[PDB]
Length: 285
Ligand SMILES: [Cl-]
Image 1 (cartoon, rainbow, N blue to C red):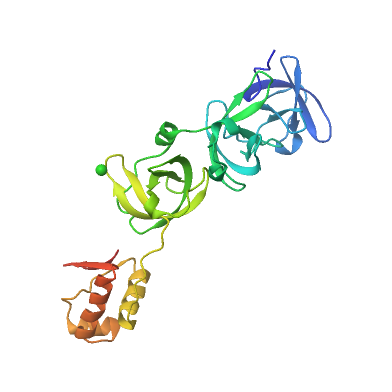
Image 2 (image 1 turned 30 degrees about the vertical axis):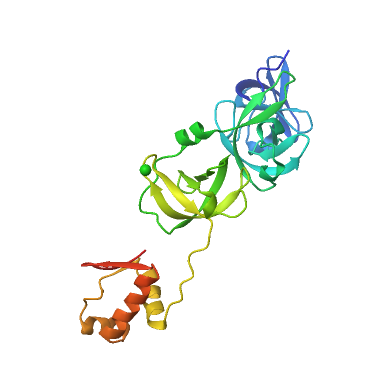
C-alpha cells in the first residue's frame, strides 16, 4: 500500500554512495540524499525528510524543511495549471508541491498567480502523491501576534491569505501581524496569495489587527516653508520641540523664518493632516 514514510522525518542507514548521492535505506526502500547537503559516511545513520522528486525518485533532504504534514511553510507559486491547481516551491530539493484546484477559489481571477505566496502544509494521498493544503484563519491567528497601535501611516508588505465579500485578510510577514483591507480601500479584488504594499490606516481593538489601505495618500500641496518643516521632521525622528508657541529666537535659529511665517507653515501642515502639536512640540503623523 502507501509509503507512510513519505513527507516525514526518518532515520535511515547509508548503504551506498556515488559522486552525487548518498543512498539511504529505510523499510526496504532507498532514498537519495544529495552529497552537496553535507558529509556523511557509508554505514552510518542519517536523519532527514523523505519525499519524492519531480523525476519520480525517492529522496531524503537534511536541509531545513518548512512545510511538512505537521507544520505550515511558505511557498512561492511557480506555475498555474487551470485543470490541476498551482505549483509552489517550499524549498524541497527538486520538488514543487501542488495545491489542488479543489481548494482554490472557483473564480480563476482570484487564483494565485506565478510569484504569489501561499502558506501550506503537506498531505499524502493513497497513490503516494504529495499535495499542499492551505492554512485557514485559525492557523494565521495561531502564527501571528497581536498588532501594535503605533503603526499609523507606515507601509508594509502584506500577503493575502483569505478572501471574503466584506474584505481581504492579510498577513504582514515583516511584523508577524494580521490585517484587513475593506473593499473601499482597494481597487480590483485581491487574489489569493497576492503580495500587497499596504498602508496602516487604523487599529482594530477587538482582535488587535490592523486596518489597511492600498489607496494613495491624499494629495496635499505644501508651501515651501511647510515642506522645509516636513523634511526636517522626517530627518529628525518624526519629532521636534518647536511648535506654534515657540519663541521667535528658537524658530529663527532652526528655520531662518519669522514666527508668523512659521505659524502659517504649521497651519498648512495641520490642514494637510501631516502633524499634530502639544506642549512638547510637533509630531509627524
Ligand atoms: Cl474594536
